Amino acid sequence: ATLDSEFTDYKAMFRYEAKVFKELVDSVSKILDEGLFIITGEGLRLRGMDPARVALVDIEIPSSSFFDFYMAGDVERVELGVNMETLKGVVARAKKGDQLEVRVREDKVLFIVESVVLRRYLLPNLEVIVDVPEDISLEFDATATVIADVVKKTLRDVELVGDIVEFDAGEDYLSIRSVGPERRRVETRLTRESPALIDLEVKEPATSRYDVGYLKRMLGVAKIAESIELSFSTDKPLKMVFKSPDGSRVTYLLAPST
Image (tube, rainbow, N blue to C red; front, side, top):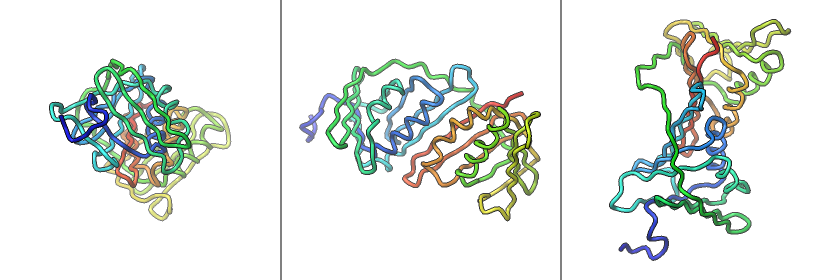
């Protein structure tokens, strides 16, 4: 027994901003149908690949980013398996200042959303298969921090004229461009004089192509961060990291079009 008198069969609980959680959920739903969240003393983590193994999403909310957070004493790790379409339903109404509370046991997951009304949901805790790529030294030849709205608008424009986007980094610039025969070719060239280019480090030149449809879906989460940290190498995966001011983090990995 604990000094808590409410919800004493649950193994973990947290409280968080429902609107930010809705944005984190949506970011995952672009990649995964079902996700396995893990709750530990460090906070909340999810990582998984889509079925084609072409894209990955990784969510981290440090325990210090939560309004409240605790785990039962006999437990180091608590899994939360959930379908992302169902979870969007739970937090669909969310506005600024609405709080979400989540309590987790092995067989069930309680969600309480404080919105216009108090919404309560009780979900089964799903068994979810996690697939992740092999853990190796991923080397990135090129890294750039860019204002996220500029990347999103670039991808919008590229998609007008083709379905592949090329990232071209030289020593002192980053070019994002459409390819293929439709005209005019769209090109956003950033240099260290561009306000949009916060930082650029290029170890070696890198040129890679990616599915713009997929990247566009990924940039849906741009409204959680002012800037995006991009990393890539020639004919290797692009990594994109969105760092929220509250400390939560969304990372994506996207395999190249070859």
